[PDB]
Length: 574
Ligand SMILES: [Zn+2]
Ligand SMILES: [Zn+2]
Image (cartoon, rainbow, N blue to C red; front, top):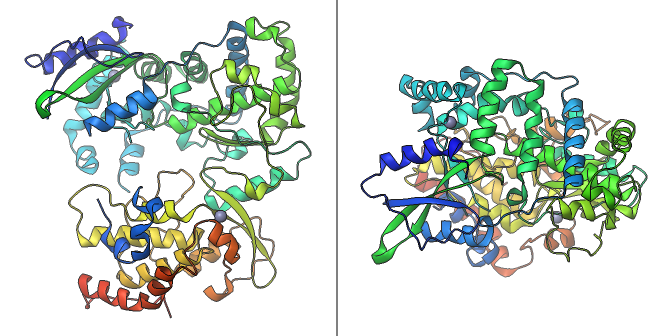
């Protein structure tokens, strides 16, 4: 461990728990440095009541110190092996080229306290309105400008692993690197292959556009445990963005990168004897600390780099000898300057997910650089060629597939779809304990309106959404977080009529809809074919679902009585 960079944080934690601090020789950490330990100490009722048939669907009901330790042994206690020197030379060249393209029409900048407060306002609200929080933030920034870090420490939670950091550390990351998100550096117009800021209502059109580019099949390979495969070399290559920063901003960003990305200090819970719990203090110099302000943007960047490299190997620009040491590097510069933009426009990359439309199917067996970079494909033998898709409507991307549907008048739209159990299961989860009827119903309304905008083509979701919206007062504003996906843009977070929002999103503002004729009734908005709806998890035709549909108005009346019969309600079912 680099005690010169993490030592201050470990010593600070040790001094805060000095009387219970101890070194456990029987700790379970294999690839993380261990420093010591100390002693340490959910249903949305509205959605549940309106989704009775799914109480026995394991796909729905399925989705702590023991939990944190399980994710360590199953996923995070691993070390990605170093790529060879030539592979590292290619990764650095491609990353340098890509940063220069992304920065051609954009300038890095510091993000402000005002920008952060505005994003928070959408107990974090209490902290941003307290001057003592900003004083703690200022003390840590002063340490950073002096080459020190005292409190940027992760808190592991898990259940993929989720790494939490105190709001002030997240502010310092946002100040230095938030411009990647706020100024849309990974937007498609700026990056060619990125899709940041496109909603699920548009991603399908990107895949359809890619299908028309001449080339091989569409490949959408997943890397097994992407965040654990981000190496110290990937982090150094991502850090090249600091070369485009002015000196003051550069100092802030280098502190975030060096002290919190390239060196990390984490707190993890672990069960101990007699039902007691300990907190372990560990560290490491690689992996992506999933949950950072710029995890998505940096994962998108590095996945773009990986896919450009796999295309160069497929096109026989890179040879086997180049893994050991890159020979004739001008060939890589030429390929990037000549073909890089064309190959970026042949990709759709969102964090660790990608779809590539290579110039031919040599991409399927171009595995040497991919495997040497440790970006090993999930659910496939390491050296077996990839299998691509001939039909863009079957390609998985961002946990969805995309289907062309036809409106009653002959026009077509391209909609997002996924297996329905995950959609209902997520809506049935309420975040945090102590949620009242007002907060629970507003969050149920947000899921229901999101379904009306994006998944209206699924029979069960259109009906369940109409039942939820009929059970929650119409003047209640949808609240909470409907998804963690950057592609759920929140047009459904409104009291504007969802048929109006549907028309704005799918017709008026949809650049892929040439005819702007409005759709004036929900009965003119299509469903998937019954067999497609069933393939993706519908319960149509299943007796408990038929009973639920026939009883739905009774169920809505029951919920209205619970919330209060005096509220303003709208009948969305008739
Ligand atoms: Zn710090
Ligand atoms: Zn589907």
